[PDB]
Image (cartoon, coloured by chain):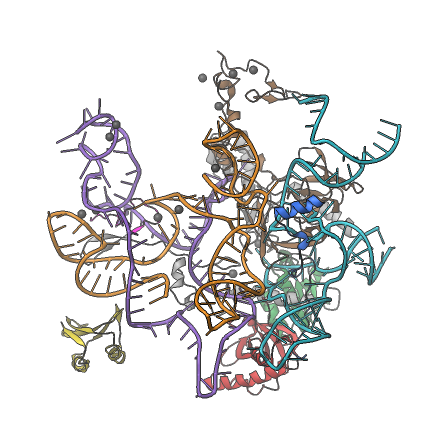
Chain colours: B blue, D brown, E red, F yellow, G green, H cyan, I purple, J orange
RNA sequence: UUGACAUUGUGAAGUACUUAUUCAAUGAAGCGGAGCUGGACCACGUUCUAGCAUUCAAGGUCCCAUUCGGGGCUGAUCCGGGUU
RNA sequence: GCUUGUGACGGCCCGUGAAAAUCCACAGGAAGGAAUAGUUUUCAUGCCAGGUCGUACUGAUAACCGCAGCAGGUCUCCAAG
RNA sequence: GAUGGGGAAGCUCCGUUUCAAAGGCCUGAUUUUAUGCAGGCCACCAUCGAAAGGGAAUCCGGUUAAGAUUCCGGAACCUGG
C-alpha cells in the first residue's frame, strides 16, 4: 500500500514523464523514470521492419558497433532482402531488353 | 587498347545529366552592370 | 437472424435526422465500406482510406478514385473518350 | 454603428487559413527545356490525404536534368492514377490519364484538369474534386485554344498552357449529407473560422443593416448595387434576378 | 532444352553475394547427401576491377585491375541464369565438392581462380562478366 | 559489475598495472541437497570495472589465495 | 476455343500450376508450353519469358486474369501461370494456342 | 465611378512598332537567326517493368619533356551577349 | 481482481490526427595504402577534463489571489481491507 | 522581429527571401611567417519563441536542528580530447 511520487520537477503525465514502480534493496517502493521505447528501423522500399538491426533511440546508435547496425549484404541496413532481390531482377531484365 | 573502352554519353532530353556549359548569356549580373548596359541600348 | 427490417447500417442513428436523409446516407455508407476487387493482383482486398483513396491489402498498391466508390461513372466515360481520341492521333 | 462581420475578415486576425497539416501547395513542374521540347518521365510514389482539401494528392518524383539528385512534385491526383505509375510531362507526351501536355497538342473533346491560365503559372483551373475542363476548339494561326470551364463559361487560353489528362479524383463528395452540426464543425476546423453563421436579422441595428425591429425582418430590398461601399454590401449583391 | 550447364553465367540473388555475377562450374541436379536440393558449384567475383583510362600510369593500372574471387555452393532458386557463357576448363579441376568442407583447400582453389580471371580480363573478352551490375 | 569464470584470465588481471586493490569474500551457502559448504569470491578492482571470480571448492581456493601477487593490496573479508 | 483445348489436356495430359513449379520445370527442360495470365506483373512476366527463351519454350498469353485462368483449368483458386509438361489427346502444342 | 490634362514616344491608312510604364517566373539553362544531317514546309538520341544515372567524361586527336600527371580542340556546329 | 505498461488486431471520419535540431545505415569509389613492413581508435584495456544559473519552505478552511490567518477562486502524479 | 529595399512631414510603417555583388569548412600550394595563393564542394542567406512538445549520460545504502538522484561510501554511464 506504499505510494510513490515523481522524482523530477515535472508533475504532469507526459510522454517524457513516465514511471515504473520498483522495490529497492531497502525494502520500499520507489518510482523509476523510464525512457520512451525505441522503434525498429524500416525498409526504404516497402516500409517493413528490418531484420537483424538493433532497436535504439537515434543517439544510441553512435555508441554501438557497426555489426549491430547492418547486414552482410548489399543495402544491408537500408533495404530488406526481398526488396534487394526485386532490384537485382529488375536491373538485369531491363538492361537485357535495352540491348534487343 | 585492351583495357580502355569507348562509352559515349547521351545528352538528350530525359537522358544523362547535362554537362557544364557556358552560361554567360544567362548570368544574373549585379544591378549596376545591367543599368549601364541598358542605358546604352 | 435478421436484426433490422430496412435501416441496415443506419440503425446507429436511432430515430434522428429524418428517414429520407438516413436513406441517402445508407446507400453511400455501404459503398464506401465495401470490399472491392484489385485490378493488379485479382484479389478482393481493396478498401477505402480517406475519401478518394483506395488501397489494396495485398500487393500494397493505392489507386486514386471516387469519394465513396473506387470508380465513378463520369471517370469511366472519360477513359473511353481518351482511348478513342488516342487512337485517332497515332493511327 | 460598429464594423460589421464581413468587414472584420479583411484584417486577417482570427480569419486566416489553418495550414498546419497541409501537405504543401499543389502545383505542376516549372516550365523548363524538357517540358517545352520533349517529355520527362516521373514516378508516382504515394497518394495521400490533404487536410482541408477533398481531392487527394499525388507525390511524383522526377530527376533533375542539370545536377544529380531527385526533385519532388506535388500534384492533384486524377482518377485511375496509382502508385508505381510512370507520368510523362512535356510537349511530346502521350495522350494518357495523368500525363501533362500543352493544350495545343491534344485533340478536340479532350478532358483535362489543373489547367494553366497562362504558360508557367503551374495550374489554376479545375482543381476541386470531380471537376474538369473540356477543350472545344483550336486557333493555330492565333496560337489560341477555346475551352469550357466547370461553371459553364467559355474562355480563350494560350495553346502553350499545360493541363493534366483526366478528371480530378474524389468526385461525388457533396452528394452525402453532413446530417449533423458536428460534422460541419470538423469540416471547417481544418479550413478557416467561418462557421457557424449568425443571421443578420437576429442582430441589433448597431451590428448589421438587417438588425432591429419589433419583428425579425429585413425592411428594405436585399438586392444591393455593385457601387455600394463597405458596410452596405450585405445580402444579394448586384443581383440580375431573384426567386426560384 | 536444358541451360544449367557447366559454362552458364548466372547472377546471385541472395546471400552476401546478391548482385554478383557468377559462372557455373559443376551442377548437381538431383541433390546430394548434403544440400538436399538442386545446386551448382560456382565461382564468381567479389571485387570487380575499377575503370581504367589512358591517363593512369603503369603503377596504378595494375592496382585497379585486381580481382577478388570467391567459390560458393548455391541453390538453383538463388541464381538468375543469363545467356552468356565462360569457359571453365582452366579451373574446373580445383573447384569441386572435396575443395569445400576444408579451410586449406578453399584458399588454394581461390588463388587458381584469381589467376584465370585476371588473364581473362586482360585482352578484353567476356566484358559483360567483368562489368559490375548497377542496382 | 563483471564476472569471470576462467582462472587463467584472472591472474592476468592482477598484473594489469592499473589494479591496486582486491578483496576476498567468504560465503556460507547451502548446496542443492547436501551439507553446507564455504564459497569464496575474488574481486579485483579495475579502473573501469570490478571483476568477480567465484569458486565453490575450498581446496582450489587456498591455492589461488597463495598465488596472488605479493605487491597487490589484498583485503581479507 | 482455348478453354476447350485447355480442358482436354487436364484430363489426359500432365500440367503444372503456379509460378514456382513452372520455373522448376523450365530449368529441367520438361516444359513444352507456358500460359501466362493477363494481369501478371510485368517483372514476373518478363522473367518467365527470359527463362522460356533460354529453354526454347513456346509462350502463350491468356486473355484473362488469374481468376479466369483458374476457372479454365478447372480449379476453384487463382492461377497466375500454367506449365504444360506433355499434351494428352489434344493438339494445343501444334496450333496457335 | 466617369471625363480632361500630365506621365506620352514611333509608322501607316480611312491598326502597326518598341524603348517608357505594367504583370509573371526562374538559386535568370538552352532564346532568336542561320547552318548540317533526314523526311515530306516538319523532324533531327528518352514510353511493356516502383532498378540504375554524380568525380573538368570515356574514347579520338594535338602539346609537355616523362613521374605519380598536366594543357588545348573534338566529343557537345556557328552567330548576336535581348534571362524568359 | 485493481493500477499501469505493452503487443497483435478491429471500429470511426467531406476530421486521416506537428515541426526542427540531432544520430545512424546504404549507394558511390576520390584518395590512402604491405614484406622486413603497415593500417584499423565503429574490438578490448589504459589517461585527462566536464563551466554558468536554479535547488530551503508553503502549495492552501493560515505561507498564492480576493483590503484579512475571508465557508470563495486556483493546473497535476501516487491510491489499502 | 533586424538586415536589403519601398512608404511616411515625422514619431515610425510594410515585409522575412523579399527587384541585394548577402557567407565559410576539407585540404592542396609554402619549411623566408604565418597563412598569401591553386581545382572543387556548398548557396541552405539574422535572431527570438516550450522549467508539460523534441532531447547525449546514475543508481542503491547511509548521513543533518534545518541539505541531497546535488554531500559520504560503493557501484556505473555519457560527451569532448
Ligand atoms: Cl458580427
Ligand atoms: Mg521536456
Ligand atoms: Mg436580440
Ligand atoms: Mg446601420
Ligand atoms: Mg439600408
Ligand atoms: Mg526541496
Ligand atoms: Mg496580494
Ligand atoms: Mg491587491
Ligand atoms: Mg517590422
Ligand atoms: Mg531559442
Ligand atoms: Mg528537505
Ligand atoms: Zn523492403
Ligand atoms: Zn492488389
Queried whether the magenta region covers residue E49, the answer comes back as no
Q: Residue furthest top?
A: D214
- Left or right: where does residue D88 sit relative to residue A4? right
Name the residue: 50% across, 16% down: D211
- Name the image quarter holding residue F18: bottom left
Queried whether the magenta region covers residue A6, the answer comes back as yes
Q: Where does the image place residue H71, in percent across and percent down from the top left? A: 65, 69
Q: Give the range drawn in magenta.
A: A1-19
Q: Nearer the viewer, residue H6 or C32?
A: H6
- Left or right: where does residue E62 sit relative to residue D40? left
- Left or right: where does residue D65 sit relative to residue E47? right
Q: Where does the image place residue B1, in percent across and percent down from the top left? A: 68, 79
Check the image and report above or below for D222 versus J23. above
- Name the image quarter holding residue D114: top right
Check the image and report above or below for D150 versus H62. above
Q: Which of G25 and G92 is in front in this view?
A: G25
Asked whether residue E96 appears in the rendered view, the answer is: no
Q: Which of H64 and H15 is in front in this view?
A: H64
Split into 4 quadrants, where in the image is the N terminus of chain F?
bottom left
- Left or right: where does residue D243 sit relative to residue H3? left
Q: Quadrant of ligand 5?
A: top right
Q: Which of D56 and D37 is in front in this view?
A: D37
Name the residue: 49% across, 79% down: E34
Amino acid at each position: 500500500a506504499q505510494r510513490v511520487t515523481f522524482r523530477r520537477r515535472n508533475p504532469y503525465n507526459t510522454r517524457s514523464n513516465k514511471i515504473k514502480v520498483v522495490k529497492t534493496p531497502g525494502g520500499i517502493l520507489r518510482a523509476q523514470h523510464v525512457k520512451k521505447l525505441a522503434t525498429r528501423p524500416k525498409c526504404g522500399d516497402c516500409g517493413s521492419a528490418l531484420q537483424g538491426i538493433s532497436t535504439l533511440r537515434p543517439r544510441q546508435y553512435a555508441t554501438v558497433s557497426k555489426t549491430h547496425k547492418t547486414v552482410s549484404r548489399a543495402y544491408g541496413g537500408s533495404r530488406c532482402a526481398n526488396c534487394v532481390k526485386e532490384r537485382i531482377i529488375r536491373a538485369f531484365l531491363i538492361e537485357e531488353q535495352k540491348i534487343v | 587498347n585492351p583495357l580502355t573502352h569507348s562509352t559515349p554519353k547521351n545528352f538528350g532530353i530525359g537522358q544523362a545529366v547535362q554537362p557544364k556549359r557556358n552560361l554567360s548569356r544567362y548570368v544574373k549580373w549585379p544591378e549596376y552592370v545591367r543599368v549601364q548596359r541598358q542605358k546604352k541600348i | 437472424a435478421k436484426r433490422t427490417k430496412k435501416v441496415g447500417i443506419t440503425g446507429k442513428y436511432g430515430v434522428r435526422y429524418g428517414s429520407s436523409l438516413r436513406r441517402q446516407v445508407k446507400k453511400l455508407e455501404i459503398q464506401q465500406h465495401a470490399r472491392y476487387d484489385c485490378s493488379f493482383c485479382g484479389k478482393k482486398t481493396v478498401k477505402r482510406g480517406a475519401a478518394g483513396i483506395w488501397t489494396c491489402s495485398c500487393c500494397k498498391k493505392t489507386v486514386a478514385g471516387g469519394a465513396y466508390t473506387v470508380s465513378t461513372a463520369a471517370a469511366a466515360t472519360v477513359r473511353s473518350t481518351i482511348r478513342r481520341l488516342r487512337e485517332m492521333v497515332e493511327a | 454603428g460598429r464594423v460589421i462581420r464581413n468587414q472584420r475578415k479583411g484584417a486577417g486576425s482570427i480569419f486566416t487559413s489553418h495550414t498546419r497539416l497541409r501537405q504543401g501547395a499543389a502545383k505542376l513542374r516549372t516550365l523548363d527545356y524538357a517540358e517545352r521540347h520533349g517529355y520527362i518521365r516521373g514516378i508516382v510514389k504515394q497518394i495521400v490525404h490533404d487536410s482541408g482539401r477533398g481531392a487527394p494528392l499525388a507525390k511524383v518524383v522526377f530527376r533533375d536534368p542539370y545536377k544529380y539528385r531527385l526533385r519532388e512534385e506535388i500534384f492533384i491526383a486524377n482518377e485511375g492514377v496509382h502508385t508505381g505509375q510512370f507520368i510523362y510531362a512535356g510537349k511530346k507526351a502521350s495522350l494518357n490519364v495523368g500525363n501533362v501536355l500543352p493544350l495545343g497538342s491534344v485533340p478536340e473533346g479532350t478532358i483535362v484538369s489543373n489547367v494553366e491560365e497562362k504558360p508557367g503559372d503551374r495550374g489554376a483551373l479545375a482543381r476541386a474534386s470531380g471537376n474538369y475542363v473540356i477543350i472545344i476548339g483550336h486557333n493555330p494561326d492565333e496560337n489560341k485554344t477555346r475551352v469550357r470551364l466547370p461553371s459553364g463559361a467559355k474562355k480563350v487560353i494560350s495553346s502553350d498552357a499545360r493541363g493534366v489528362i483526366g478528371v480530378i479524383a474524389g468526385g461525388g463528395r457533396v452528394d452525402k449529407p453532413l446530417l449533423k452540426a458536428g460534422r460541419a464543425f470538423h469540416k471547417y476546423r481544418l479550413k478557416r473560422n467561418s462557421w457557424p453563421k449568425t443571421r443578420g436579422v437576429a442582430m441589433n441595428p448597431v451590428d448589421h443593416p438587417h438588425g432591429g425591429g419589433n419583428h425579425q425582418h429585413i425592411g428594405k430590398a436585399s438586392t444591393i448595387s455593385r457601387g455600394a461601399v463597405s458596410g452596405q454590401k450585405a445580402g444579394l449583391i448586384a443581383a440580375r434576378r431573384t426567386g426560384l | 532444352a536444358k541451360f544449367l550447364k557447366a559454362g552458364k553465367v548466372a547472377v546471385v540473388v541472395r546471400g552476401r553475394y546478391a548482385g554478383k555475377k557468377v559462372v557455373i562450374v559443376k551442377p548437381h541436379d538431383e541433390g546430394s547427401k548434403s544440400h538436399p536440393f538442386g545446386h551448382a558449384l560456382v565461382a564468381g567475383i567479389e571485387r570487380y576491377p575499377l575503370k581504367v583510362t589512358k591517363k593512369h600510369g603503369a603503377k596504378k593500372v595494375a592496382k585497379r585491375t585486381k580481382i577478388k574471387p570467391f567459390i560458393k555452393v548455391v541453390n538453383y532458386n538463388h541464381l538468375l541464369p543469363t545467356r552468356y557463357t565462360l569457359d571453365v576448363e582452366a579451373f574446373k579441376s580445383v573447384v569441386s565438392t572435396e575443395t569445400f568442407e576444408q579451410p586449406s583447400q578453399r584458399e588454394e582453389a581461390k588463388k587458381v581462380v584469381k589467376k584465370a580471371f585476371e588473364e581473362r580480363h586482360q585482352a578484353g573478352k567476356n566484358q559483360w562478366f567483368f562489368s559490375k551490375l548497377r542496382f | 559489475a563483471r564476472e569471470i569464470t576462467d582462472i587463467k584470465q584472472f591472474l592476468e588481471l592482477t598484473r594489469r598495472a592499473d589494479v591496486k586493490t582486491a578483496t576476498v569474500k567468504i560465503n556460507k551457502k547451502l548446496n542443492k541437497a547436501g551439507k553446507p559448504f564455504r564459497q569464496t569470491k575474488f574481486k579485483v578492482r579495475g579502473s573501469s570495472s570490478l571483476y568477480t571470480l567465484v569458486i565453490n571448492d575450498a581446496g582450489k581456493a587456498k591455492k589461488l589465495i597463495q598465488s596472488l601477487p605479493p605487491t597487490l593490496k589484498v583485503n581479507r573479508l | 476455343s482455348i478453354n476447350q483445348k485447355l480442358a482436354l489436356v487436364i484430363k489426359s495430359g500432365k500440367y503444372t500450376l503456379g509460378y514456382k513449379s513452372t520455373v522448376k520445370s523450365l530449368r529441367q527442360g520438361k516444359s513444352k508450353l507456358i500460359i501466362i495470365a493477363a494481369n501478371t506483373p510485368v517483372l514476373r512476366k518478363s522473367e518467365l519469358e527470359y527463362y522460356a527463351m533460354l529453354s526454347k519454350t513456346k509462350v502463350y498469353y491468356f486473355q484473362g486474369g488469374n481468376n479466369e485462368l483458374g476457372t479454365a483449368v478447372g480449379k476453384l483458386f487463382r492461377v497466375g501461370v500454367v506449365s504444360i509438361l506433355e499434351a494428352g489427346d489434344s493438339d494445343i502444342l501444334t496450333t496457335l494456342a
